[PDB]
Structure formats: structure tokens, C-alpha cells
Amino acid sequence: SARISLFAVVVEDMAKSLEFYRKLGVEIPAEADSAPHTEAVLDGGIRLAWDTVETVRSYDPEWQAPTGGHRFAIAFEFPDTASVDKKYAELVDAGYEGHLKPWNAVWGQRYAIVKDPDGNVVDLFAPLPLE
Amino acid sequence: SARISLFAVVVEDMAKSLEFYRKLGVEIPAEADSAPHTEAVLDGGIRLAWDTVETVRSYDPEWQAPTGGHRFAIAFEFPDTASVDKKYAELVDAGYEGHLKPWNAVWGQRYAIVKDPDGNVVDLFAPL
Image (cartoon, rainbow over all chains, first blue to last red; front, side, top):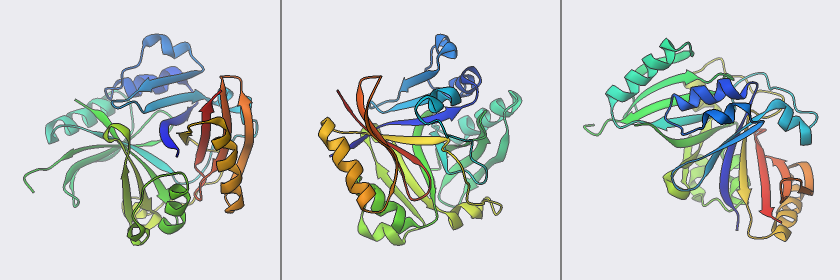
């Protein structure tokens, strides 16, 4: 039986994408900026990977950047409301797109949304245990 | 302080999506087919989630089904190489999109690529 081993995102610029994720706590060496493909190991073993458009086209020649609504989102968990809000402001202050400012979501979590350098949706959240 | 916790995909049809993933060994309750949101816990606690387009258009009324290549891919590892070819044939027979047929990738893996019901790329692999 199969098991999910890795998740990957296609990036226009490796260095630019990597710096955004480093800002979200993902451990990535600076040296990876010059790589056509980068992988980071998440807690538990699953990997998050980045492949440049050229790398993708090496085996998937007809690949074209999609237009329209996002097909997915990557959600990061924080310990509390303070850390979520602080990170949102930090990312926006760093030049990244703040899509939806922090709010208390009906499902019981402090929630916020930003976009990565490639325009992908990234959620920031923390539980609201008092609810 | 921050850690990746979830990877979510937008589905036009929850049932159609979930049945594809159940075919890849993802344990998903049958009643999740009628839910606007579904989650499955993977190795280490990270979750794969599904959200209907309506759920999505809630906080994004503009959302329009995209077209084009993937910006995101999910890679499934298999116990052996024969399992990769077998699963690829099965999924294609089930009516799913076979993108790139099995081959011995230069990085040292039997590799194959299909697309899920919503256009997301799914890699099938096993070490050579």
C-alpha cells in the first residue's frame, strides 16, 4: 500500500520561494538557493520540495503555469494568536501579500492568509482553546 | 514556533476526489463524501485536506476553476517497483488521467504521474 512521502511546489525562482518559507520556520540551507530542486524534511519524515519550472519541464515538457483559482493551500500552525498576528505583519512588512488579515474563524482558530512568491495560498493559524 | 500542519486541495466534487485518493491507500470514511471539508492524518501528524469549491468561494467568491499545469504535486511511495506500474494501470482503468507512463527516472526511481480529478499532479514512485 502506498504512503504520501512528499509534497512539491513548482517555483519560478528558487531563492525567492525559499526565503519566504524560511520566514515561516522551514529549515532550508542558504546553499539551496542555487539548486534546481530542493527538499526539506518535515517533522515525521514527510518532505516539502521545490522544483524550478525548468526542472519540471525536463520530464514534463508541456507544463504551463495555470491560470484561475488556486488548486491548493499550505497551512502553518502557530502556538497562539499572538504568534499568528505577529507573523502576518512580519510577512507583509517583508513585502509579501497579506490576503486576509487575522480573524477569529468560525471553526475556532485564529486565522490569516498570505500568498507565497509564486502566488500560492498559505494559511496561518492557531487554535483558540478557550472556545 | 511555526510548523507545517496541513496541505489542502480544492475539490469541485468531494466524492469524486475522495474516491480517487482512497484508491491510493488514503483512509477516508465513506460519509466524508457528503462533507464540505475532509481531513486525513498522515505520518507525523501532518494532514491532507479537501475543501469544496463552495467552501472556498466563501472566502473567495471570485474563485474560478483553473486550467494549466500544476503548481502543486503529491508524491506517493510504493513498497516495490511493480506496484507503481500496477497502480498506474489501475487508476487509468478507473478513468483517471494518466499523465506520464511508468519509467526508470534518472534519479533512481520507478516513476509515474497521474492527475487527480481536480488537476493536481500525483507522483507514483518506488526506489530502483
